[PDB]
Amino acid sequence: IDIYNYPNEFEDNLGSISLGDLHGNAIKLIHFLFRHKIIKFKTEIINFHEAYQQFVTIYEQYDDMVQEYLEIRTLLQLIQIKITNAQQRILDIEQKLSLATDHQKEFSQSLLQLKKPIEANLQMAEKSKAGLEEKLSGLKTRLPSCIERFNKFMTQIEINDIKTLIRLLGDEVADRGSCDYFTLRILDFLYQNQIAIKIILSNHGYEFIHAYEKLVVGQPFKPKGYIGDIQIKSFWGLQLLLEQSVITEEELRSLVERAYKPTLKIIDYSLSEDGITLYSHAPIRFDSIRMAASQLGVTYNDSTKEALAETIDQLNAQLQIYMKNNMLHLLFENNEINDPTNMTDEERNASPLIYLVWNRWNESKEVENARPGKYNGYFVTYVHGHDPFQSPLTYVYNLDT
Amino acid sequence: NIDIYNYPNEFEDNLGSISLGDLHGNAIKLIHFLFRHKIIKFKTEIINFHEAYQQFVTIYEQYDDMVQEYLEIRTLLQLIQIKITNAQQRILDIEQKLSLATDHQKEFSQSLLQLKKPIEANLQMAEKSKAGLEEKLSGLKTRLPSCIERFNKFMTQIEINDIKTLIRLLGDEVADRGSCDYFTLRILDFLYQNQIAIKIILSNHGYEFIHAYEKLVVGQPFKPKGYIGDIQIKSFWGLQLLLEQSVITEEELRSLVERAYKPTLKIIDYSLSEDGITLYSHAPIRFDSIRMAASQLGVTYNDSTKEALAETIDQLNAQLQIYMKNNMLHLLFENNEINDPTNMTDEERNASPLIYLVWNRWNESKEVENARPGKYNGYFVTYVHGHDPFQSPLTYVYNLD
């Protein structure tokens, strides 16, 4: 499908729809909501295609502004290395000078002479940096027009279908897209309209949550850093607005606390009369559910599909306790992991949530043992976000929605 | 080529001065060197000089093997303590959150205790792993005092012979691949009490030692800079091992360093012939580099006559003694902006000339007519330097080994 044009085809649905991989791309979310008739343009809007197009334009301009923000961050880190080196030498010297008594005169003079050239280099570096942060002020001047164009675009939208469950299988924030502010504003639009939305926890998602949990305890609103800056560009689109005071912290906390955080699940399910469907981010293994229970102190039971449904509900409740206390990072701190995408049985038992958000499938993992299509008498169906490997099982669903 | 592992049968007189090129932190090389040039002799009551010599060499090599064991131990403990700091920071992290927890949190506190448990298990197993190696380590502490007792016996057997000769050590006298710096420092002390003129040119390995000592005396751990790997500054760890195991007190170490080693240290040295100057250095260096040292140290540079160059060099070293008396030589040897100390660019050696002086390696390209002139102004210049693989063909460049 072409997400950069207003949809010409529309899909009715069966009470729930899943978005497999958003890539932090608000255009894909808007396009997905139009295509499934969750939202619609209001009557006074005539040219639907043009209306959709102005959001496309806003989004791409903002994307290039974030690109420039990334280049500036790289350069700031580079110049900060030199600033740090000169500052360290000057600090040591100034300590040795500050403890100079009247007896050590030639001593003080010698330290002064050694300090002068380093001070010069530091002045030149510090001011190259002054140039960079000037260019950054220049960007601050330009973002508000883009945001006002975005709000104007949102004035043209209204809800249509309210009886459909929306499920996002991950990478809705902190990803390749343009700006998480757009996405959270769309999710808040859905919240204000009492739309049912569930979001499955993912690794990009965790980068975002990690930044948010740092922010609420007074640390910078900046992520863990396991994923590189380009691959979480959309997070930086949001962070940019915060640090430049274009939006307020209370607005960000409002959107996150009311529209994002209550939607998160470790795993979701739905019940049919004869089985259960498990929705996750990454392709995972049946036996991982029990492991996650062990980490969260949730008593595991899968004797019936209802017993598994209850187990998953308890997992998600415990998750929400970690979200309410902004301490989900305690469950993703494990430095002893070689490859989170290819975690060993020991690593999986030690940090199961990490496995659930990072696992990437391949054929060595495709083994008859991994994902049964029936367990304890009930059918099991697996649905997860886009993963390159394409399993031939007919009860496994790899969504590029 | 000498055989340093047996008492010398060859002997050679001196022509005023005497220079040792490659110490490598090996006290056997220095003892043999002092014997062959007849600076020291065995006392009359010693009959078999060969056997008395063999005593020292055998304690030297057994002590070497003990130092290797200490290295294995210390690497292991460093890793285990990384695990211990990791855990500890988190039992404290969560514990702070349980302390933050309200009385209103039953399930919350339950989950956090449940999650504390595994890290505490790991912390206990790691702490045990450490305890075992500590037991072994003092299991070596019980053996060191034998080695040092017999070293003291050997030292009682020597006495001074020639006292009208100047000895020049071109560097790498400490913190090198030898066995123990305590032996070398004791030998230097012995020459000191016998009023022998000794000069040491400071080197890179030398600076590793000095950095460790400057850290020591202001109260931080006696730990080296760390550019050179540990097995390559092994003799330093040989000394540190006795200091840490209380085989020798801090006060003996500091008396030794302060009076027997620190006042000897030159950075460039010279003897004056009738028609010229001969320049004593550690690394192969350029003539102009001398000037930039004065630039970094604010000494008035004058080389119009061999005596002007002499006195300028004297105030160079006087300034360095300022830097030792105040234990701040690190300020001249810490510059992380330098890409490569073996091949420093012009701006780098003007920025940190002494780093160049102790690190520079000569090669085919560096030998240019401008680099090391044999006659300059009205006086000849002869260069001497510590061992370096490249071999210059100029009749006034001597690369000792």
Image (tube, coloured by chain):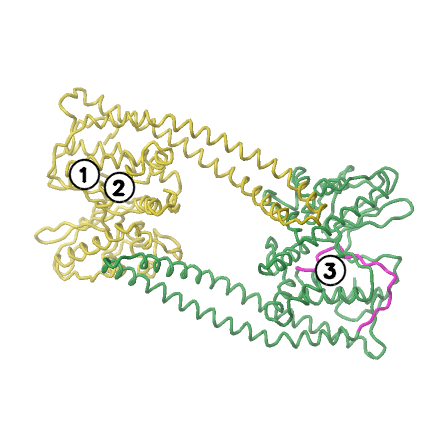
Chain colours: A yellow, B green
**Is A220 drawn above or below residue A70 in the view shown?**
below
Q: Do circles 2 and 1 both sit on a common chain?
A: yes
State the image coordinates of residue B181 (x, y, percent, origin top left): 68, 64
Residue B318 relative to residue A171: left or right = right
Numbered mark located on residue B261 in the image: 3
Q: Give the left or right position of residue B61, taking residue A300 as reference.
A: right
Q: What whole-number distance in Å separates the C-alpha atoms at marks 3 and 1?
A: 76 Å
Chain ID, mark 3: B
Q: Residues within 10 Å of mark 1 (few under 14, many from 20)?
A: some
Residue A343 or residue A361, whichever sits in front? A343
The residue to which callout 2 is attached is: A256
Mark pair 2, 1: CA separation: 11 Å
Q: Earlier in the sequence, mark 2 or mark 1?
A: 1
Relative to residue A297, is residue B128 depicted above or below?
Answer: below
Front-most of residues A401 and A211: A211
Residue bearing mark 1: A191
Question: In terms of image quadrants, where is residue A89?
Answer: top right
**Span colored in magenta:** B158-175
Q: Which SS does the magenta portion mostly show?
A: loop
**Residue farthest toward the left in the current orientation of the protein:** A273
Few, some or many residues within 10 Å of mark 3 (<14, 14–19, 20+)? some
The C terminus of chain B - image quarter: bottom right
Q: Amino acid at mark 1?
A: Tyr
Q: Is residue A185 left or right of residue A109?
A: left
Q: Amino acid at mark 3?
A: Tyr
| Residue kind at label 2, given as amino acid type | Val
Q: For the residue labelled by badge 2, is the local secondary structure a helix, a strand or a loop?
A: helix
Q: Do residues under tags 3 and 1 come within 8 Å of each other at their CB atoms?
A: no
